[PDB]
Length: 513
Ligand SMILES: CC(=O)N[C@H]1[C@H](Oc2ccc([N+](=O)[O-])cc2)O[C@H](CO)[C@@H](O[C@@H]2O[C@H](CO)[C@@H](O)[C@H](O)[C@H]2NC(C)=O)[C@@H]1O
Image (cartoon, rainbow, N blue to C red; front, side):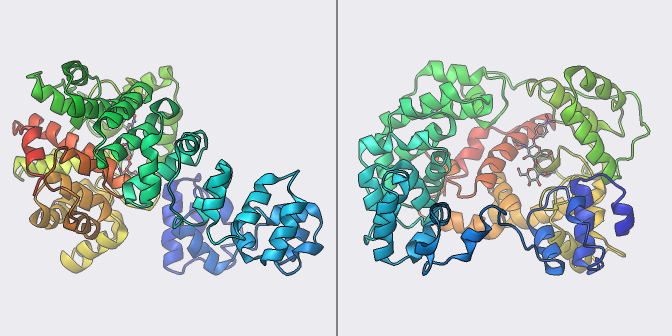
C-alpha cells in the first residue's frame, strides 16, 4: 500500500505500522511527510524518530513564556519574576547557577515559593538531598530523585510515612526495590506504616520487607495489598504471600476458591486437593462469515468497536463472530463480555501444531494466548506481528536467512501456519538453553541475554526460604515479570486440556538451581 492509500484508512496501529514500513524503506518524500503527524495514531518511538529525520520538530515552547527561554544562568537575574520562577522548574538549570545567585534567588522566593528557596539553597551544599530531607520537603525530594537516582540517604519514620501521598511514590518504590538500588532508601521504607499505603505500593513494600527478613512487616503489607487491590489476580498474589509467610489455612482456602485463574489460585487448588477450574468449551457450528481474518485494518476497526461496545452491543457482536473462521474474535468478545470471570482457552488453527508433542503444543498455545489472544493480524505498539508477536528483525532473520522461504515478507507472521512454525522454531532455541517454561517465557518476551544475566546472579532462582516465589517478584523488567506469571498459568491449563497434566509444584521445584 502506497502512502495515498494509507491516508484513506482510519488512524490505527496497523496504519502506523505501514507508514513505518514506508519510512524505513525511504519511500516517504519530504513532501509526503508534511501533513503526516495528523495521520499517525501513536506518535511515539521509532515512527517518530524516523519521521523527524525528514522533518525535525521545532516545538515546543509556549508563546506566553518564550521570552523566559532567552535567558541563561548568566543573565537570569535580569529576567522578570515570572521568568525566574519558570526557569527554576528545572533542577539542571538550578545546578548550573553560581552559588551567589542561588542565594539571591533563594531570598527573592522565600515567601512566595519556599519550594524554590529550598532547592536553591540545597544546591549550595555538597548534598542537596540531605538538605531537602532535613526540611521534609516532599515535592523537593521527588524532583531530586527524578534529577538523579544516585542520591541515597537514610530517611526517618516521619519522612518516609509522608512519601506515599505523592504520585511519584509508586514508581519510586517499585524502581528501587526491583532494581536493588538506593539501599538506604530501601531500608528506610521498612518503617512505612501499612495504613499509609495500598495496592501495588503496599505489595512492593511487602517484597522489600522479605528481602530484609522482616516477615511480620511483610505480612502486614501484603495483607493491606490484598484488601485494597482492584484486580482479583493481584489480590491472589498478595494472599499467596500472606499464606507463605504465616500459613493461616483460611488464607489458602480463600486463595483456592478464587474466581481468577492464575498461578497462585492454581497452586492453592493443587495444595488442597481442589478440582482443576472449569474451562469453557467453544465450538461454533457455523463455519465462516464475511470477515477477513487476514486484513489488519479490519481487525483494528472491529477491536475498537468491541472495546467501546456497551453490554448489549457485545451480545450482538458475539452472535456475528460465532463461527469457526472467527473463533479468536468470538472468544475475545466473550472474554470482554463476561467480566473476566469465565475461562476461555481456545486452540485455533490446531492443524498446524497437532504433530508436535503435547508439552510443546501447550507452550506455543500459552505464549500465543498472552501475545495476541490468537488474533492473526495483531500488532503491538512496537510493531511485533501476528499470533506469536514476532519483532520484524527476528521474523526476517528466521524467514530469509534461516529458513530461506521464497519471497518472504515479515507480514507472513500474520499467517497462523507461519506464526506457529516460527514460534516452534524459536521456542526450541530457547528451551534447549533454559529448560523451564517460565525461563523460556521470560526470554521470549525480554530476550535470552536479559534472562541469562538474571539467572547468573547469586540472589535469583537459587535456594531460599521463599524461593522460587521471591525471585519471580524481583524479575527486573515489569513487562517480563508479569508475562512469565501469565504464560505459566496458561501453560498449566493447556497441558491439562491436552490430557498432559503436570503439577505446578513440579514446575516450581525445577526453578531452584
Ligand atoms: C493485562 C494483560 O495481560 N493484558 C494483555 C491483554 O489481555 C487481555 C486482552 C483482552 C481481553 N478482553 O478482551 O477482555 C482481556 C485481557 O492481551 C494483549 C493481547 O491481545 C496483551 O498484549 C500483549 O502483551 C505482551 C506482553 O505481555 C506483548 O508482548 C504483546 O506484543 C502484546 N500484544 C499486542 C497486540 O500489543 C496484554 O498484555
